[PDB]
Amino acid sequence: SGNKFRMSLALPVGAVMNCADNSGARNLYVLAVKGTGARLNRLPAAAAGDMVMATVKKGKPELRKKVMPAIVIRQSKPWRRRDGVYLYFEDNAGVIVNPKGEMKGSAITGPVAKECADLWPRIASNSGVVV
Amino acid sequence: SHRKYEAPRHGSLGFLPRKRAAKQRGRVKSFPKDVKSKPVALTAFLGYKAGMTTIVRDLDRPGSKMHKREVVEAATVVDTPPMVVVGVVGYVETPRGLRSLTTVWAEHLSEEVRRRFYKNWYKSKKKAFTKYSGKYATDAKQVETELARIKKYASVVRVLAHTQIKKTPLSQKKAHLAEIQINGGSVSDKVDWAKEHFEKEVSVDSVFEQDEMIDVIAVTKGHGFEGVTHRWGTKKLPRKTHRGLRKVACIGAWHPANVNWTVARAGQNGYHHRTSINHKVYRVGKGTDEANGATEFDRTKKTINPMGGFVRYGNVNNDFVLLKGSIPGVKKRVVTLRKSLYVDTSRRAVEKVNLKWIDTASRFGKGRFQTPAEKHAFMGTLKKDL
Amino acid sequence: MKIEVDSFSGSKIYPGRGTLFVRGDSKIFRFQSSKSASLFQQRKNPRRISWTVLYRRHHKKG
RNA sequence: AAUAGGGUGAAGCCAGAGGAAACUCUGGUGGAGGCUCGUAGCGGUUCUGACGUGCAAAUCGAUCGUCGAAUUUGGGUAUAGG
RNA sequence: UAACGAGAUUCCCACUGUCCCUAUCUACUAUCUAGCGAAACCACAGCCAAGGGAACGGGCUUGGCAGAAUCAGCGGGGAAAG
RNA sequence: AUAACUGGCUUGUGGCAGUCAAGCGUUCAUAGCGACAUUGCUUUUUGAUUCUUCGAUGUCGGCUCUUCCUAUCAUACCGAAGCAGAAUUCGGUAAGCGUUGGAUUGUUCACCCACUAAUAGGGAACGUGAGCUGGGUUUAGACCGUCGUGAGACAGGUUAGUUUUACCCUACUGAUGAAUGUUAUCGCAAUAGUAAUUGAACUUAGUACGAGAGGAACCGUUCAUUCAGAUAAUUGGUUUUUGCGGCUGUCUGAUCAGGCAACGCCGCGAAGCUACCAUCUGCUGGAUUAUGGCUGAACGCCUCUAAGUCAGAAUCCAUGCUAGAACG
Ligand SMILES: O[C@H](c1cc(C(F)(F)F)nc2c(C(F)(F)F)cccc12)[C@@H]1CCCCN1
């Protein structure tokens, strides 16, 4: 439920990002991106605010070895906003959510991109600093 | 056998052959269709690509997430001093297409446009248009007869106009002469307008208004002979391939026992004629205005020129057109600006543009000042300042 | 449009110029160019970089 | 006839400590080995690199095995077509 | 089965243009010039579609067509060469 | 004269499609199916044959790339339902447009994970090796198992095993060019090509429909996917600007200033080039197919059809875009 402008993709399939919520996961390994069309040889890739299918590579055993949706909340690849600003974060991080976009954890450590907070109200609720 | 997997074709078959343009001046392939009820007006203009800049603008697009919020946008500056009208051509409708009936010229042509007709001007006797200038002897009935022929038989009337390239920083002395179709009014009205404008200047403000969507006709940047990988965007072959990898691996099946015209091949890249449409006019600047780059929010008395001049162009001391985005061609290229061929009622086409700020920092580096006065205020006194 | 200030060198940042850096501790740094951006990621001290505003105010120049 | 420079640190030997004894422990010294890192040398793993009417009827480049012995090599000499 | 292995294989950390997806730069070629100057190969030669045909034609039949001389590339064909 | 590829005749077998209509489908042969029979098509399977090639047509698969077929997976417009809505199934015009990222396997095939509007099937010497690669097979080394007295065999497993040449003709891609009195400028447009594509969110609307459960759509708005053509504002990349600075070894007696390290190394680095790693742009008219209609006979009624005629698809032809006939 939203229309965010195109952003430079930061996380191809196979990328491992940080897990920024208290859900108990420490890694989030991207294996697919929601909304990725067809193009030969092109890897699906995610930007901040994208829903992702991910596994927990490092974390609690009951969180490990499962496919689960996740949302990227910050990215280290610089991207341009429509106001001309190129910005980037120190790392790539995401949070575990439902298919509906509702978090599993209850807090987020670190800043959150405004594209993601503007696009996912629950992450905005559980988010602190939003840049 | 079929392809194992599908993929779209690399490149467009509608821009073949990828050869050099026959002329460097882009030619208007089609002019806007004539409506008699409109007033008599020009439909195109010739300018010179000066450079690119940056603006800040408040967006007026309801329903957008950037509505009423500032956007930073690339813009192009086109140096456009007024063109001089020197002639008029009549075209006749024939079962084989349009046919030029007669060309009538003005009595006096400037040296810059008369150099157009010479390859070695300095070695010439400069005889161009001298007998024709004598044709105006004390009654000009030959000229009146040709004009009457145009009124009687022509269905399409085009004027001949040339740029005043001496007002630009270019070292070229030849003017650029082009046919610009006249739209509006009857054929007699068009011929009268052309005659009354012989040897007269026509400014940009009489052809283009602000917020218009216009087309740009130009010859793109040349790249010379190019391989398939960059000419057509084909996939590079694996690293361990013998005899090289910037190739197309299979250029055809066994049958047809020929290479097809649709296979990507190495060849000349760039320097193509392109027509790019729907570029919005953010500003029609005036050359006499000393605050070209100033807006209603940035009251700095400031021209459009960056610090140190446009890189590899110079300063824009004339009237100019500020277009949104990028247009084909390189710096100093002559560009033909054409009015739109259709009526666009989309919100992007009908939006009224009010500029917030225009970038005039140096384009020759990471410029960080908008004005020498600002530079002096920031840095204070230097050693060279006594 | 408003003019920002380079966090490293103190130079004026005009719309679209330079980059925005968000540190892990949620602090926001603005660099007018890749020169000061590179010196910042190289951990240089602007008080010890002779052309920055911080150096010039520390040394009472101009 | 030839084979840089290092590492490791075997027997043997000196001193000290513990023990009733049988014996044990510690610090040096010493300089062994078809030991080891690595040059010249000898070889020829991979790039399935270059070249492939070649510089060359087997070479060139990087990478690599080994490098004090079952080592490398000159000359003399012996073995000759079922 | 400790040690050893330019032996075959699986996984993990580090690492990276292997890849997403490409871009840019350097020297030597290629290129153009003066001088020098080969070889493979060669029935005759050299534009296509269908037909029939030793059952996949450059030549035949029926059509499409067809305008000197050429340069750099290229690898579809000559069921190319060896 | 004769096997192992391609190709040719054939089409048993493989694949696909019809006709009849006993039955299934609460009733009800034909919404959707359809036994017993029976008529065909195809050459994407495998056989059969041995016509071409043994003074050699490089024999698997993958990568790359173009194009074609339609027996249509999606997208456009529609007809039918055991179609209330949503979903789904059957079908028509339709190949314009797309049809993916991966784990295992040398694999074709397969099988899962996941995204997606969809993850359709095929052809072009089972397309494509002077395009690559060489994992497999199928030379020579070696091991095992079974077989053999043995040398050795295995269509069984395993490991290592040189992939040569274009400078000719044509064809493709680009580039000049004699002569059509000379030269110069501005044009016309025959013909050839052609380009855009799909999705999501908001609104409509928790509305129509429905007992409820559930639950649409047109007009519109904002964005995005795949593709295309440009461009260098900005940001990023690149650095022989060897531009500025720094550092090591050595050499010029020291200093200054320099040489060399087969660009000595490092930071920044303008300019140029360049990236869905950046930004911009991608048109509107007519004629139709299926289909639904109007008037209207044949056949005093009826009937979209016979004459005439209306609307109407991602279709076609134009508009627009690219080239400009080097004998217009
Ligand atoms: O049996 C020899 C041989 C065969 C083959 C193969 F079967 F693979 F093609 N390859 C050979 C090779 C090869 F190049 F490694 F393939 C080298 C030497 C002899 C070979 C023959 C003997 C006649 C002369 C040519 N080589």
Image: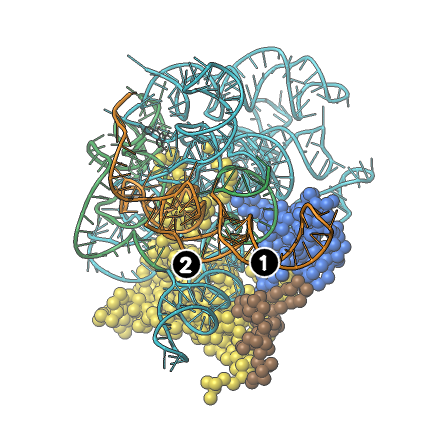
Chain colours: A blue, B yellow, C brown, D orange, E green, F cyan
Q: Residue at x 71, y 59 (%)?
A: A109
Q: Quadrant of ligand 1?
A: top left
Determine whether the residue tagged by mark 1 lies in a helix, strand or loop. loop
Nearer to the camera, F82 or E39: E39
Q: Quadrant of the C terminus of chain A?
A: bottom right
Instruction: Give the image location of residue C57, x and y in percent.
Output: 60, 81
- Mark 2, chain letter? B
Label of residue B175 in the image: none
* Kind of residue sitting beneath label 1: Lys
Q: Is residue B26 above or below residue B127?
A: above
Label of residue B220 in the image: 2
* Kind of residue sitting beneath label 2: Thr
Instruction: Give the image location of residue A33, x and y in percent.
Output: 62, 48
Marks 2 and 1 sit apart, C-alpha to C-alpha, by 32 Å
Query: Where is mark 1, residue-wise?
Result: A77
Determine whether the residue tagged by mark 2 lies in a helix, strand or loop. loop
Figure quadrant of residue B334 = bottom left
Figure quadrant of residue B142 = bottom left
* Labels 2, 1: front one: 1
Lateral position of residue E53 relative to residue A11, left or right: left
- Mark 1, chain letter? A
Lateral position of residue B205 relative to residue F28, left or right: left
Instruction: Give the image location of residue F144, x and y in percent.
Output: 52, 25
* Labels 2 & 1 near each other (Cβ < 8 A): no
Figure quadrant of residue F139 = top left
